[PDB]
DNA sequence: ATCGGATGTATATATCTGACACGTGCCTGGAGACTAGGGAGTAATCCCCTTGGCGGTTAAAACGCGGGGGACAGCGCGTACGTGCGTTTAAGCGGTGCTAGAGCTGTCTACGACCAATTGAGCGGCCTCGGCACCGGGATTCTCGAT
DNA sequence: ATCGAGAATCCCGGTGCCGAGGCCGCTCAATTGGTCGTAGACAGCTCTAGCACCGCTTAAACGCACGTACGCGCTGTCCCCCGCGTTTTAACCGCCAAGGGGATTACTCCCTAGTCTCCAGGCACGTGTCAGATATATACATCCGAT
C-alpha cells in the first residue's frame, strides 16, 4: 500500500465541529486548510529561529514564539492569539 | 515539436479574463500585449519548476515543483498540496 | 466580592433544597475552603460507603473551576492515592454556568459508571476491564475499612 | 495541571502537541526547543483555524449550502480586514473574485 | 425594429456573471500545448503531471485577472473607460515587474 | 408577551440581568459576565460552549455587544434596581 | 528692467542639482524629535542610538524619493506635469501599500 | 517632557527638495499634507517593529541593528549600518 | 591538489573556506555539511564581490577619484542590468539616485 | 574586549587584484560586508530548503549549485556556476 | 536669428586636516590525525500513471455588418503655483557635566537531550446514503423605444 | 416626467449519482521513567555613550507681491468597438492500449561528526601622511528680450 502521509484533517474537522456543529467541508477546502496551517507554522517557526539567533541563544521558548506571533499577525489577531497562547501555556503548566 | 501555440489564447479567452477583472471596454491592441506578458510569466515560472525537477533527478514536472516555484516568486498557491 | 456573593447564593440554594445523597459546607471560618460528604449510590457496589472530600475555591470564581480532592482512600480507576479525581467536567470542559451541585452529581454518576476511555490509572482500569469479581471484592474490602 | 494524560488535553487544545513538538525539533529551526513552545504554537494555529472556519461557515450558510467549498473560504478571507492582510499574497484555487464594479462604469 | 441592446449594457452583464463564478476561463488543451512548448526549451523529453498543468493555469489566470484589475484603475485615472496597452505598461512598471 | 422577573436572569450572576448580550446561539447573558469570561475563560458560550471569537472581535470594535431591544424592555419595568447595582 | 527666469527653468536646475548630490534633505533635529515622539507613543521611556535615528532617516528619505518618482509617472500618464494627491493615492494602491 | 505636533517639522521646502530629487517639476498645493501622512504611517510601521525587537531582548535603547532587522523584515533591506 | 597548503590557497580563492564551513555548520541549516560546499560558496561570493568592485572602481576612475564611496557603488549597481535585478529591493546608504528627467518636462524648442 | 569578524581584508585583497591603484573608504567596506552577508544567507537558506524538499540531511555542492542557479540571473548564474565548479575541481585534486 | 547683458556653472591653484593604510602583539579559532557509524549510492522489482489514438457532438471560435458612443484635438478662461526679496526663526556647531545602562565575568541550578518499552492515536481501505447538480416550467425584474 | 413588449434571471419541484463521513484493522510514533551534561539565570562590576544645558552664527524657513502658463470645461468630428446573425473549427468526452518512470526494498562502503593537540592568522591598537574638501580668482555655457 501507499506510505503513511500525515495531515491536519482530523484536527481541522474537530475544530470545525465546534463553531458549526451542522456543517461539512469539501476535500479541496480541507486541502486548502491544510496548506494554510502548514504555511503559518513555517512562517512563525522560521521567524522564531532568527529571533533566537539574533540574541545568541540555542533554545526556542514560548517567549520567542510569542514575539514571532506579535511580529507576524495584524493588530488585533496578534492580541487575540497571544492571549490564547498564554492561556494554553498557563493551563498546561498548572 | 510545437510552434506558435500562443494563438490558442484567443480574443474571447482574454475578454472573459478582462470582464472578471472588471473591464467594461477593451481596445483592439490589448490582446497581443496580454499574450506577451502571459508568455513572460509562464517562462519565468516554468524555468524554476524545471530547475526543481532537474535537481531531484526526475523526468516529470510534479505539482510540488510548480508550487515551490510559485512560492519562491512570491505567489503562494493554496489547493495543490505543499 | 462577586465570588463571595456567588458562594452565598450557592449556600442559599443548598439550604433551600438539600441535594441528593451529598452534603457540602465550609469546614473553617473561610468560605473559600469547603468539605463535602458523599454517600454511596444505591446502584453501585459502594453501598454504605461515606466519602469525605475537600473543596478549594480559586480567587477568580466561577471563571476558574474549583479543585476537589478525596480525603479518604477509595479504589477506583479515576482516583489516585492522593485523592484527586479524573473528570473532564472538572477541568477540561468547565464553564461558569455550572455549579458545585452539578460537579458533585457528576462525581456521583462517575461512581455509578466509571470512565475507561481516559483512565487516570491504567493498571486498575485494566483490572476493571478484565474481570468484575476481583474488582468488586477489593473495592468492597477497602470501602469496608476506609470509607467508614 | 496533573500529568499522566495526553498533552493535547492538558492544554485544552485540539491540535496535536506531540506532532508540533516533533516538527519543531526536527525542522532545523534551533539546536534545542523549549517544552512550552509547542503548546503556544498549537494554540495559535488552532485559534487561526477556528477564526477562518467560523467565517467560512457563515458564508456557506448565507448561500443556503451546508458544505464549505473554496469559494466560501475566499469570500470569508477577502471580507475581513485582518485575514486579508495576513493572506495578502496568497491565491486560493477555485476561489474567484469579489464582486466590485467601479462607479464610473455604471450607466447614468 | 428587432430588439438590440445599447452598447455597454451587455459588457456589464458579463462582468456581473463572471465575477460570480469560479471556473477557469481559458481552454485547457491550448494552454497545455503552450506550457509544453514553453518548457521544451529548458529541458527536452519532459513529462508533466496532470496537476502541474492545472496549477500553472490557476496561477496564470489569477495573475492576469489582477493585472486587468490594476489596468482598469490606470485607465479610469486617465479620465476614460477604455483600457489601452499604455495602461498595462504603467501598471507593470509601478508594481515592479517592468522597471 | 412581557417576560416575568424569574425568566429574565443571567446564569452566572444569578441576580438581575443588566445590559444583555445575545450570542449567535441565542443564549443571553449580562455584559459584565461576558467581559469577565473573555479575559480568563475559554472565550466560548458559557451555556452551550460555542465559539464566538469572531463575534467578539466583530462587535467589540463597533461596541454593539449589547442587545439594545431587550435592554430597554428590562430597564423600563425595573428601574429601581439600577441605583443599588 | 530686472532679470528673472521664466517659470520652469529653476525647477529643472534644482532637479539636476539634487539628483547629483547624496546628502540628506530633511533637517535632522525635527526628524529625531518626530521619531522619538512616535516611539514614546509605542513604549514609554525609550533611548535611541544615533545610528538608529540615522538609519530611520535614510530609509524614510529613500522611500519618499521612490514614491515621488512613481507619483510623477502617474501624473504624466494623465497628460499633466503637476503632481496631485490622487497620483500618490494611485501609486500607493497599485504598489499594494493601501489596497 | 512629552512632545506634540512635531510632524510640522517636515517643512514644505524639505518635501520640495525630495520631489526635486525624485524628478518632479511642478507640485500641487495639497501634496504636503498627503506626504506627511504617508511618512507618518511608514515611520509608525517601522518603529513598532523596532520597539518589538528591542523589547524581546530586555533592553531600553534601540540599537541600529533593531531598525535594520525591522526594515529587512518589511522587505526594505538597508546596507550601511550592519547586518 | 597537494593537500598541504591552506584551504583557500589550495582552492585558489581569497575568501576563507574554514570560516564559511563553520558558518554553514553553526547556522542551523542542515544536520550535515558536505566537504565541497564551502569551496563552492566561497568561489561564488568572491566572484560577485570582484564584479561589483570592478564596476565601482570603473565608476570612481570616471569620476576622477581613487577611492570607492557609496555613490560609486550605487552607480555601478544601478547602471548594470543583472546586478540591478539582483539588488532590486536594496537601499544603499548615502547612495543617491540615478539622474534622469522625463522628456515631457524638458523645455520646448 | 570583543572580537568581531568581518570580510574586510578579503574584500580588500580582491579589490587589489582588480584595481591595484584605487583605494576604498569605510562606509563602502560596511556596504560590501552587508552585501556579502546577505548573499551568504540567501544562498544558504535556498540550499537548506532544497535539501529538505528531497528528504536529504546534507548540503553538498550540487545543492549550492542549484541554489545559485535559482537566485542569480542568467549570465551571472552561468558565470558563478563556472567559477564554483572550477574552484571545486581545483580543490579536490 | 542673433544681438549683447546677465546669471550660473565649470576650471585651475594653494593648503591643511583627519581618515586611510600599514606595523605590532597575541590569543582564539582553524588545521592535522584517528575512530565509528549511519547516510547515501546502486541494483532489482512492481505497477501506476502518463502518452497516444479514434470517433462523435456540439459548445465555442471566427467572420461580417450597421452604427452609436467614446477618444482626441482645438479654444478659451482664470486661478493657482513659480520666482525673487526682505524678515524672522531655530538648526548647527563647539564645549561641559552626569549617570543610566549595555557589556562582561563567575556560580550554579534546573531544564532539555538520549535511550528502552509499550501501547493507543491516527492512517489506509470499504461502504453507504444524502447533499448537490441538473432539467423543466413559471414568475420576476431590468431594458429600450415611443408616446 | 410615463406604458408596454422582448428578454434575461430567479424560484420551485422532482430525479439521480458520487463522494463525504463513519467504521474496522493495524503498525509506529508518542508517552513514561530515569540519567547526565550544560545553557542561561542571577548577581556584581566597569566605563560608554546617551541625555541635558548654554552661547553664537548664519543658514534655511517664512510671508508676500506679481504674473503667466497650465488645468479644466466645452464643442466638434470621425472611426472603432459592440451587439447580433451565420458558418466553420476543434474542444471535450468516452474508450482502448502500452510502457516509462516513480516508488520501494535490500546491501554495502566511505564520508562526515566528534575528540584532542598545536600554532599562526586575523583582530584590537597605535601612528605617519596625502586625498580631498574649501576658499579664491578666471572662463565658458546658457537664458532672455527683440530686432
Ligand atoms: Zn451576570
Ligand atoms: Zn450558547
Image (tube, coloured by chain):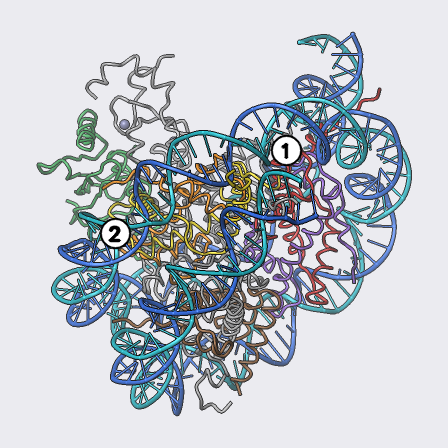
Chain colours: B purple, C green, E red, G yellow, H orange, J brown, K blue, L cyan
Residue at numbered disc 1: E79
**Chain at tag 1:** E
The mark closer to the camera, 2 or 1, is 1
Q: Is H51 positioned to the left or the right of C36 in the image?
A: right
Q: Quadrant of the N terminus of chain B?
A: bottom right
Across and down, in percent, residue K58 comes to: 81, 39
E9 up-or-down from L94: above or below: above
| Front in this rendered view, residue C62 or F59 | F59
Location of the C terminus of chain B (image quadrant) = bottom right
Of residues C15 and E51, the one drawn nearer to the viewer in this rendering = E51
| Image marks 2 and 1: residues in contact by CB distance under 8 Å | no
Residue E5 visible from this viewpoint: no
Image coordinates of residue B9 in percent, x first then y, are: 74, 48
The Cα atoms of the two marked residues, 2 and 1, are separated by 93 Å
Residue B28's quadrant in the figure? Answer: top right
**Displayed quadrant of residue C47:** top left
Residue behind mark 2: C137
In this rendering, does residue H34 appear at all? yes
Name the quarter showing ligand 1: top left
Q: Quadrant of residue C94?
A: top left
Amino acid at each position: 500500500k501507499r506510505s503513511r502521509k500525515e495531515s491536519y484533517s482530523i484536527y481541522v474537522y474537530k475544530v470545525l465541529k465546534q463553531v458549526h456543529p451542522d456543517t461539512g467541508i469539501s476535500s479541496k477546502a480541507m486541502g486548502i486548510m491544510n496548506s494554510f496551517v502548514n504555511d503559518i507554522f513555517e512562517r512563525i517557526a522560521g521567524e522564531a529561529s532568527r529571533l533566537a539567533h539574533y540574541n545568541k541563544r540555542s533554545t526556542i521558548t514560548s517567549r520567542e514564539i510569542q514575539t514571532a506571533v506579535r511580529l507576524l499577525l495584524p493588530g488585533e489577531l496578534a492580541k487575540h492569539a497571544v492571549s490564547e497562547g498564554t492561556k494554553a501555556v498557563t493551563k498546561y503548566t498548572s | 515539436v510545437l510552434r506558435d501555440n500562443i494563438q490558442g489564447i484567443t480574443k474571447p479567452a482574454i475578454r472573459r479574463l478582462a470582464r472578471r477583472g472588471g473591464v467594461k471596454r477593451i481596445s483592439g491592441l490589448i490582446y497581443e500585449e496580454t499574450r506577451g506578458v502571459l508568455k513572460v510569466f509562464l517562462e519565468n515560472v516554468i524555468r524554476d519548476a524545471v530547475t526543481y525537477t532537474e535537481h531531484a533527478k526526475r523526468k516529470t514536472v510534479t505539482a510540488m515543483d510548480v508550487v515551490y516555484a510559485l512560492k519562491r516568486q512570491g505567489r503562494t498557491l493554496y489547493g495543490f498540496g505543499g | 466580592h462577586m465570588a463571595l456573593k456567588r458562594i452565598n447564593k450557592e449556600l442559599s440554594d443548598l439550604a433551600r433544597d438539600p441535594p441528593a445523597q451529598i452534603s457540602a459546607g465550609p469546614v473553617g471560618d473561610d468560605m473559600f475552603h469547603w468539605q463535602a460528604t458523599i454517600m454511596g449510590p444505591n446502584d453501585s457496589p459502594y453501598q454504605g460507603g461515606v466519602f469525605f472530600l475537600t473543596i478549594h475555591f480559586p480567587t477568580d470564581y466561577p471563571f476558574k473551576p474549583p479543585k476537589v480532592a478525596f480525603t479518604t482512600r477509595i479504589y477506583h480507576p479515576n482516583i489516585n492515592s492522593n485523592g484527586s479525581i479524573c473528570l473532564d467536567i472538572l477541568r477540561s470542559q468547565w464553564s461558569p454556568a455550572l455549579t458545585i451541585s452539578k460537579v458533585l452529581l457528576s462525581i456521583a454518576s462517575l461512581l455509578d459508571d466509571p470512565n475507561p476511555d481516559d483512565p487516570k490509572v491504567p493498571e486498575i482500569a485494566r483490572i476493571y476491564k478484565t474481570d468484575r469479581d476481583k474488582y468488586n471484592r477489593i473495592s468492597r474490602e477497602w470501602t469496608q475499612k476506609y470509607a467508614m | 495541571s496533573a500529568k499522566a494524560c495526553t498533552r493535547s488535553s492538558r492544554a485544552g487544545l485540539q491540535f496535536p502537541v506531540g506532532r508540533v513538538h516533533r516538527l519543531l525539533r526536527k525542522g532545523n529551526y534551533s539546536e534545542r526547543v523549549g517544552a512550552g513552545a509547542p503548546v503556544y504554537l498549537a494554540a495559535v494555529l488552532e485559534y487561526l483555524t477556528a477564526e477562518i472556519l467560523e467565517l467560512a461557515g457563515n458564508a456557506a450558510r448565507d448561500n443556503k449550502k451546508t458544505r464549505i467549498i473554496p469559494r466560501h473560504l475566499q469570500l470569508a478571507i477577502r471580507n475581513d480586514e485582518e485575514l486579508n492582510k495576513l493572506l495578502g499574497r496568497v491565491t486560493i484555487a477555485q476561489g474567484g473574485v469579489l464582486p466590485n464594479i467601479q462607479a464610473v462604469l455604471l450607466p447614468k | 425594429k428587432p430588439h438590440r441592446y445599447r452598447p455597454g449594457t451587455v459588457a456589464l452583464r458579463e462582468i456581473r456573471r463572471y465575477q460570480k463564478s469560479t471556473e477557469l476561463l481559458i481552454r485547457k488543451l491550448p494552454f497545455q500545448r503552450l506550457v509544453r512548448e514553453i518548457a521544451q526549451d529548458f529541458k527536452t523529453d519532459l513529462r508533466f503531471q496532470s496537476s502541474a498543468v492545472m496549477a500553472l493555469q490557476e496561477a496564470c489566470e489569477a495573475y492576469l485577472v489582477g493585472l486587468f484589475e490594476d489596468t482598469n484603475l490606470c485607465a479610469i485615472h486617465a479620465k476614460r473607460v477604455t483600457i489601452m496597452p499604455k495602461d498595462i505598461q504603467l501598471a507593470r512598471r509601478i508594481r515592479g515587474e517592468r522597471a | 408577551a412581557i417576560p416575568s422577573l424569574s425568566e429574565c436572569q443571567c446564569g452566572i450572576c444569578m441576580e438581575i440581568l443588566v445590559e444583555p448580550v445575545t450570542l449567535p446561539c441565542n443564549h443571553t447573558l449580562c455584559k459584565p459576565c461576558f467581559q469577565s469570561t473573555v479575559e480568563k475563560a475559554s472565550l466560548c458560550c458559557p451555556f452551550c460552549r460555542r465559539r464566538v471569537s469572531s463575534w467578539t472581535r466583530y462587535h467589540t470594535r463597533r461596541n454593539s455587544l449589547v442587545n439594545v431591544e431587550l435592554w430597554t424592555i428590562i430597564q423600563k419595568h425595573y428601574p429601581r434596581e439600577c441605583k443599588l447595582r
